[PDB]
Amino acid sequence: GVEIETISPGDGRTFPKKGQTCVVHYTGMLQNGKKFDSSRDRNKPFKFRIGKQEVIKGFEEGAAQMSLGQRAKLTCTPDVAYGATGHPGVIPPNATLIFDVELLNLE
C-alpha cells in the first residue's frame, strides 16, 4: 500500500532504475506522533541503491514512483515495514509511518 501526495516540482521523466544509486533527503514522522528521524540534521543525505532490499519494503516502492527534484509524502502500511515485531525502542508494533521524502539523486 503505497500512496503518494506529490509536492510538485521536478521533471517527471527522469526515473530511477535498477543498478542505480539514489540520494534522498528524508524525514520520519509517526502518525499522531513526533519526529523520530531526520536526514536534514546529520547533513549526510543517505546514499542508497535500488533492488538489494537494504531499505524497508514500503520506502523502496515510494522512491521508484518519484522523479528528479520531486518531493513525495509517503504513508506506508504497517505490514510492509515493521508492524509484526516493531523496531526495538524506536517504533511500536503495528504502527503507521509518515515520511517527507525528496529525491535529489544522481545516476
Image (spheres, helix red, strand yellow):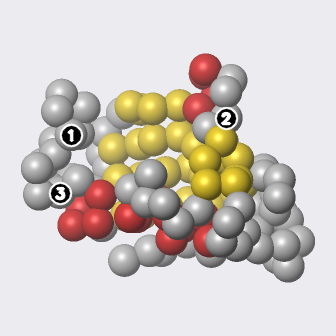
Which badge, 3 or 2, is on the more N-terminal residue?
2
* Position in image of residue 56 (x %, y %): 38, 56
- Tell whether 70 sits left or right of 39: right
Residue 83, numbered label: 3
Rendered residue at 11%/57% (across/down): 84
Residue 91 % position (x, y): 23, 39
**10 Å crowding of disc 2: few (<14), some (14-19), many (20+):** some
Q: How many marks?
A: 3
Q: Which mark is residue 45?
A: 2
Give the alpha-carbon distance from disc 3 to disc 2, as whole Å. Answer: 26 Å
Q: If the image is split into quadrants, where does the N terminus sit?
A: bottom left
As shown in the figure, which amino acid type bears the numbered disc 1?
A: His
Q: Which residue is mark 1?
A: 87
x and y percentages locating residue 7 in the rendered image: 71, 62
Corner quadrant of residue 12:
bottom right
Q: Position of residue 36 (x, y in %)?
A: 38, 31
* Residue 66 seen: no
- Decide if residue 25 is on the left or right side of residue 35: right
